[PDB]
Image 1 (spheres, rainbow, N blue to C red):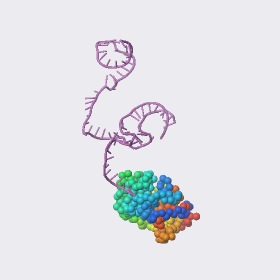
Image 2: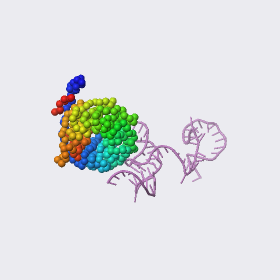
Image 3: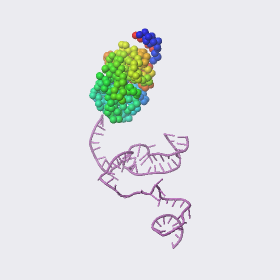
Image 4: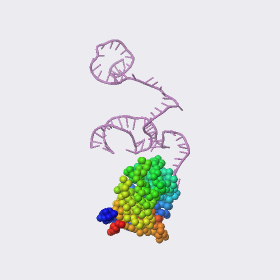
Length: 326
RNA sequence: CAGCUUUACAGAUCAAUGGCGGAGGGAGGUCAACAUCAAGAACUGUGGGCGCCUAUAGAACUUAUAACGAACAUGGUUC
């Protein structure tokens, strides 16, 4: 309609600074298909991989702190907790393990997932984590009693990212069924099922200050306030690659990594793509490989960290692009 | 052999003041329920001074070749 387009044209987005590559830390001998940082501090960030390991990394130096070898198969995801000094990690060996960070050694392997487990999210407020695998089910664990407390049946296929919010919409799943769910853990049921994607929403992330949750199928990055479970915006992601990552920055600077490796940045809520970045790879590696598989920002937000399939981790420092809608 | 404090004693006037006072058990069970027993050598309250000082106090148990055991098993997890 003309009534909306005109309005869109009238409104302007804020000039977010562009992004330039800063650090590249070829250290893993495998994909680096998870990355995470400490809520409390931003000194280190760990990165689980197809190595089977996960390595810890000092941001400032870029130096490899230490390794951790508590899986058999490849690590798919990790989550350092704000409220406790535990690092949860999870691998396609079906193990959702829990590393003490006072001793850097596993403690509570949680057992229950029938098959390769894709993501963890620690609940920001509770002493409870949430994991989901190709199982097609998101189980919540009491961390003390290392048992699945509840489980969330709804989904009809493998479930990827499964973020935890502190409100009522306490889990924000995202499947290959292309539904992204909002659940009520307490009710033992769904509350609202965002079906707006076309394909496997293989990426989703909570906004820090804004109580919303960007989510990405093969192209269209939707983003939504999950209070009602209502759409907020659609991003200009029109011919970008298969969106692997979908991290959001503190300053409303949503990042999206592709299977292409084209690092695409967007103003959040606007839905305005305001940068593209061509990937890079090593002289030995192939041009098809290069692809940002996992990524996240620091708590401040000036450094984006992208794990790419070059067996690398690339950290990114910081005139905006013209609007032009449909 | 003097002095004062307590019991055992008559019969008292019984005020005065104390102390034993709502004055009423003891010994024990291979009997329970609860609490609590590894922490700044580490305890608990009380007010007052304003999470911390200063007086009150209380305190059973376990500990310095460090422990509830002058005793010694088995698991689970990683390496």
